[PDB]
Amino acid sequence: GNTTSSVILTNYMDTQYYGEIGIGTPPQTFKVVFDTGSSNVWVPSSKCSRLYTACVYHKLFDASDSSSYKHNGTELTLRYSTGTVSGFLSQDIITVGGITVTQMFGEVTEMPALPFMLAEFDGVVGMGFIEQAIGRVTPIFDNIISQGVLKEDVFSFYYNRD
Amino acid sequence: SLGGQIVLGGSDPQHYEGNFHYINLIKTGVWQIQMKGVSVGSSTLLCEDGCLALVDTGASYISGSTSSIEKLMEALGAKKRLFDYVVKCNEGPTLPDISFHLGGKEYTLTSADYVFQESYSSKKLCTLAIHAMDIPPPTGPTWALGATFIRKFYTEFDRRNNRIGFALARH
Ligand SMILES: COCCCc1ccc(Cl)c(CN(C(=O)[C@H]2CNCC[C@@H]2c2ccc(OCCOc3c(Cl)cc(C)cc3Cl)cc2)C2CC2)c1
Ligand SMILES: *[C@@H]1O[C@H](CO)[C@@H](O)[C@H](O)[C@H]1NC(C)=O
């Protein structure tokens, strides 16, 4: 490859750094943390009841608004200290910087209010390895790697002060 | 002011200075490297033999194990609150450096890099950017270097050579 993708971040109070990504056709846009400590893409679902606080005040992905979406439905779980996170697999087209990628990801249908209600961001994109990935779903950077469009199979972080 | 930046497929020289010092992963499967010591002042108080350093862009803080943290805070002189550690705001700037031994270099965070200096008064408490976190196997037990650390050192994650790269950040 020859291209370099880059994504601007918002620094909320030296504790939360997040940037914009788009899912589907046309793109529905989300604020996410890029996590090297984790390996899955997770966003909130339109199936998340408004009775979940951690959802009501965040953005929700609606598959019913996307012409590119491809159903899977396999159920998947993650265990936090404060409770459990679950939802189901979906596939759609995700855009990060100038990069368009077909990707499997999670739609959350239930998550505890804490700490999730305190995020200014809507979800997470994991920058970790497949070994860690839940359901052994393929991580985003592996699919980016496979396209053959990056100058080098690296990525870097800059975080400002406040 | 730019809050931050993530580059895919390279780095950005405008946001660091120097060249990278690179370290190999204990094992592929996790962005985790070896750490040879944690120092308070110019003495090597903690993780003396060797410990594990998880390099976590998705965390707010530096995190150590309970054991490690009690010992770091004790050395600093901090009071433990329910969810955090605090010092009297007036002695926040009098705080010693904390140094990390990674590869062939000491990585030095100062008082200004790890204390939330909201006041300077003797009658106020100031929060530190360092918390306890017990992580379970096979990834845990480990240290974890989150935003606190990444603010001072610009970080390259290199998948071709399974190595992580450091450089002093520019602001
Ligand atoms: C610079 O970013 C630091 C932000 C610190 C922060 C603040 C709030 C939250 Cl809830 C989190 C939660 N996170 C973490 O604690 C990670 C830290 N590394 C190891 C894995 C941890 C993790 C924890 C939870 C997790 O989530 C499952 C589902 O993911 C969601 C999250 Cl985390 C938040 C919202 C609003 C919605 C969804 Cl769908 C995924 C990963 C996610 C990375 C964000 C982190
Ligand atoms: C969804 O994807 C997984 C691979 O992660 C596959 O094993 C599974 O059968 C798929 N489910 C359906 C219903 O197609």
Image (spheres, coloured by chain):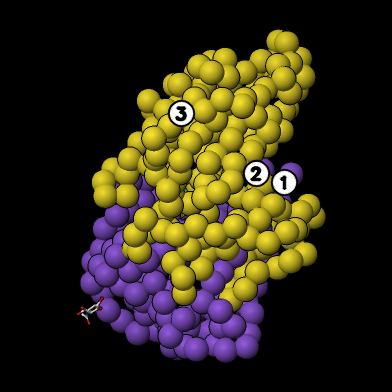
Chain colours: A purple, B yellow
Instruction: Please name the residue that numbered disc 2 is placed on.
Output: A14
Residue nearest the observer in this picture, A12 or B96: B96
Q: Are marks 2 and 1 in contact (CB under 8 Å)?
A: yes
Looking at the image, can residue A85 be seen? Answer: yes
CA gap between label 2 and label 1 equals 6 Å
Q: Is mark 3 on a helix, strand or loop?
A: strand
* Same-chain check, marks 1 and 3: no
Instruction: Please name the residue that numbered disc 3 is placed on.
Output: B46
Residue drawn where x is 73% and y is 27% of the image: B118
Task: Please state which amino acid type lies under the numbered disc 2.
Answer: Asp
* Same-chain check, marks 2 and 1: yes
First in sequence: mark 2 or mark 1?
Answer: 2
CA gap between label 1 and label 3 equals 27 Å
Residue that sits furthest to the top in the current view: B123
Residue drawn where x is 42% and y is 80% of the image: A143
Task: Please state which amino acid type lies under the numbered disc 3.
Answer: Leu
Q: Do the residues labelled 1 and 3 touch (CB within 8 Å)?
A: no
- Chain hosting mark 3: B
Q: Which mark is residue B126?
A: none
Q: Is mark 2 on a helix, strand or loop?
A: loop
Instruction: Please name the residue that numbered disc 1 is placed on.
Output: A161
In the rendered image of this protein, does residue A73 appear above or below residue B127? Answer: below
In the rendered image of this protein, does residue B72 appear above or below residue A11? Answer: above
CA gap between label 2 and label 3 equals 26 Å
Task: Please state which amino acid type lies under the numbered disc 1.
Answer: Arg
From the top left corner, tell me how far across and down residue B46 is, in percent. Answer: 46, 28
Residue drawn where x is 58% and y is 35% of the image: B99
- Residue B154 located left or right of residue B71: right
Is the shortest distance between ligand 1 and the CB of mark 1 under 8 Å?
no
From the top left corner, tell me how far across and down residue A38 is, in percent. Answer: 40, 58
Classify the position of the N terminus of chain B by image quarter.
Answer: bottom right
Residue nearest the observer in this picture, A112 or B170: B170
